[PDB]
Image (cartoon, rainbow, N blue to C red; front, side):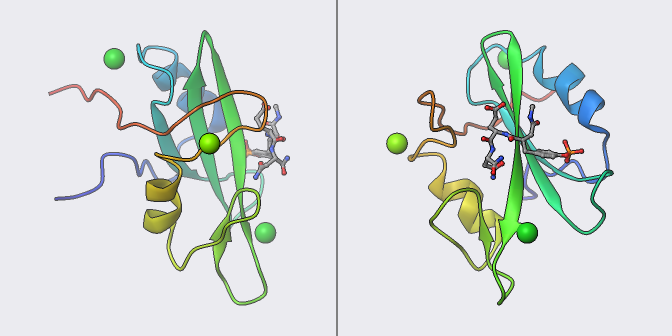
Length: 100
Ligand SMILES: CNC(=O)C[C@@H](Cc1ccc(OP(=O)(O)O)cc1)C(=O)N[C@@H](CCC(=O)O)C(=O)N[C@@H](CC(N)=O)C(N)=O
Ligand SMILES: [Cl-]
Ligand SMILES: [Cl-]
Ligand SMILES: [Mg+2]
């Protein structure tokens, strides 16, 4: 039942270390930014690179990456599983392969 994508306060570098070991493009995690307290960040695997996106907020507290906004991080993540997170490549969010 708990979400396998919330890693809390893990450094940007630790997110890259973790995702570099993932095999599939789109393997991701939501973390709580250290450089900007109170803000969330989306780290995604693509090739042997890891892309980082800042989870932006509107005036009402809704969450977005580019244009489409949501009431929760959960809804933002779910939308981005079928619509690309990147404007340069087709990267669709997929759950990480966890260590059992
Ligand atoms: C290497 N550059 C970055 O990590 C900056 C990111 C945004 C970003 C992410 C994290 C961050 O600090 P932290 O939580 O400590 O990691 C600061 C800026 C970016 O521009 N990402 C790209 C997408 C990924 C890539 O092409 O490398 C983008 O165009 N982001 C858009 C959309 C978005 N919501 O981030 C933007 N810059 O507004
Ligand atoms: Cl994997
Ligand atoms: Cl913001
Ligand atoms: Mg798309």
